[PDB]
Image: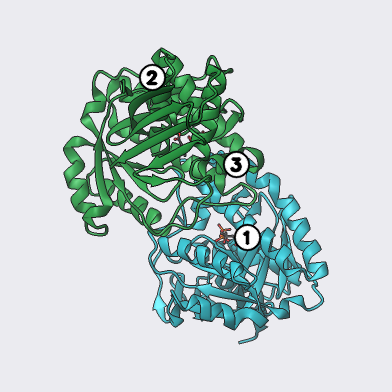
Chain colours: A cyan, B green
């Protein structure tokens, strides 16, 4: 009485950010979002449901995870079991390769295999969405858009065809180590929706940002793409400074990196930064200028702190 | 054919920020503001109007100032001469003691003396306002409020009686040296008014902040004062991240200092930060905890970077 499955899902970085839920129960977002899936960072997850198990177990990189570390996985296991009318505890074994988007997407894929759900990419995106919003985009490779929809049935992601432009781009991660303890993405976006006087200004600008990203993609206009997404990310972070109590995901090193990206642009290197719910700074750059950018940034960051990535693929399912 | 006058004016730091003009010509503000005038930093200015002068001259700390460095002083000289129907060039000699608010306030006072304008404190505040908005508050000591008014006649500052509470407080300046070239306050607030999607959220919160500062003052409630003004400052800076193009006054060291103030609070030291249009971080603290705070911050900042100030007086006029 054992069912198992495995999947590999790559991380994605949002260029137009998801920030705030319209519906917490179903993870329907207040706004649509758009990301790039990356080759360098992914998660492999195997799930086993077994009648003989006595509790849910979650192992990450060989380390048994505690209740707090397992909360999103546990919530997802419960929702997928409820849907399938499955009454068995589960063991989840995940390995990160170098992580929230990729891990929940991989778990959704692994459960789809184990429980025989036979889901389409659309409906696998919808399932992954229930575990974590950003996870629903990692079902897809390259550029992907999460359409906010208005319901559980209409909120999901899809690949954005780009005439292979994504294969000419790169993201250079600047790994910043000097951060305060940060509000989680789930708690921070909720605080922002509920209390930030800047949130309406965020919402009022998302759709025209998305439209201009699509225009830039159709024309492979890198500076235009970069200007839109850099401003989008800064606007997202601006909202947390208007929350009550206000907060920031930035650390000192984040600001240092952002300032150096501006310097890089001033010295002829077209490149544009974005940040998520933490201090790391991701820099979008054309492949042809990646090495120039890495060398420039090495004047201030160690080679361990500068990790490159190219575009990556959508989810891969495996039978056990 | 020579007329001269002198004044000394102390700097002030806004606790509720002035950010954005309703009328650029007259420097009428979009919102009212509230500051504390400080003892440690001031400017002394002597002005001479003389029929024999061949151009306006501005000397600051013994250094002849160029056209860009003189622009606010030149604009003020022109407006005060036009009002007085004075046709003489002027020499302005200023010394900073340790600077925009204090320098323009001192110049307004010196011109009031030289040209025999015989202004009340209210009308001297109105005059100084035309040179720089923050200068109109340095006419007064202690706590001062700039009431936005609706006209040149109704926009001016006044002292806020506080039953001597201001004499129990201090500001510790953390002097941060790692800053990018920053947009001036005048240009940055204009860009924010004209382009920031967050500016309405700023405006919608100013008056209730002011009201709660007045309530806290009446009760000498330091944590309440501190919470309101820290959030006000962060909200002001949040608006620049929604401007087009977006920008920040923060440097890495600014973030480091803000994080350490939060740490100080966590370790039992009540203290609250605020920033203006630059990277320095000013920390409001009770006098009784100033030395504890300075020692704590010395773990990360040099003793030259930590400069204390207490409450200071209003403008002082001198005959030459
Ligand atoms: C800042 C972001 O990374 C937010 C990611 O939020 P999460 O997907 O972590 O939140 P939940 O839906 O609560 O699981 C921007 C983005 O990825 O779009
Ligand atoms: C951020 C602030 O310091 C803005 C000061 O602005 P200025 O008084 O420098 O601007 P102008 O009126 O154009 O001369 C906040 C404050 O002092 O209230």
Q: Are marks 2 and 1 in contact (CB under 8 Å)?
A: no
Query: Quadrant location of the N terminus of chain B?
Result: top left
Disc 1 vs disc 3: which is toward the camera?
A: 3
Q: Chain of mark 2?
A: B
Circle 2 sits in a helix, a strand or a loop, which is it?
A: helix
Q: Residues within 10 Å of mark 1 (few under 14, many from 20)?
A: many
Q: Residues within 10 Å of mark 3 (few under 14, many from 20)?
A: many
Which residue does the numbered mark 2 point to in the structure image?
Answer: B113
Please name whichever residue, B129 or A232, is drawn nearer the observer in this view of the structure.
Answer: B129
Q: Is residue B301 visible?
A: yes
**What secondary structure is marked by label 3?**
helix
Residue position marked by numbered label 3 in the rendering: B192
Residue A278 position within the rendered picture, expressed as x and y whole percent measured from the top left: 48, 62
**Splitting the image into 4 quarters, where does residue A70 fall?**
bottom left
SS type, badge 1 = helix
Residue B116: where, in percent of width, then height? 42, 15
| Position of A128 relative to B192 (above/below) | below
């Amino acid at each position: 009485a054992m069912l198992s499955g495995k999947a590999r899902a790559h991380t994605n970085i949002a260029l137009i950010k998801y920030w705030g839920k319209a519906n917490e129960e179903y993870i329907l977002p207040m706004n649509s979002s758009l990301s790039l899936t990356l080759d360098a960072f992914y998660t492999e997850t195997t799930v086993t449901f077994d009648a003989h198990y006595s509790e849910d177990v979650f192992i990450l990189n060989g380390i048994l995870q505690n209740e707090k570390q397992t909360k999103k996985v546990k919530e997802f296991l419960n929702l997928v079991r409820q849907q399938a009318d499955c009454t068995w505890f589960a063991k989840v074994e995940s390995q990160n390769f170098v992580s929230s988007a990729s891990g929940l997407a991989a778990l959704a894929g692994a459960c789809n295999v184990a429980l025989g759900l036979n889901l389409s990419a659309k409906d696998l995106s919808r399932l992954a969405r229930r575990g974590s919003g950003s996870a629903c985009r990692s079902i897809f490779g390259g550029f992907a858009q999460w359409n906010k929809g208005h319901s559980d049935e209409t909120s999901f992601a899809e690949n954005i065809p780009a005439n292979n432009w994504e294969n000419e781009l790169a993201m250079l991660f600047i790994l910043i180590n000097d951060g305060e303890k940060d509000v989680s993405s789930r708690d921070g976006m909720k605080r922002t929706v509920e209390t930030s006087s800047f949130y309406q200004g965020w919402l009022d600008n998302v759709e025209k940002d998305l439209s201009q990203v699509h225009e830039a993609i159709k024309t492979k206009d890198f500076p235009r793409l970069g200007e839109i997404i850099e401003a989008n990310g800064l606007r997202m972070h601006g909202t947390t400074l208007g929350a009550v109590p206000p907060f920031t995901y930035w650390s000192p090193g984040s600001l240092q990196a952002m300032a150096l990206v501006r310097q890089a642009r001033a010295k002829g290197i077209p490149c544009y930064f974005t940040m998520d719910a933490g201090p790391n700074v991701k820099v979008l750059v054309e492949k042809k200028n990646l090495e120039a950018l890495k060398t420039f940034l090495s004047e201030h960051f160690s080679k361990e702190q500068l990790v490159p990535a190219f575009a990556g693929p959508g989810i891969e399912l495996f039978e056990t």
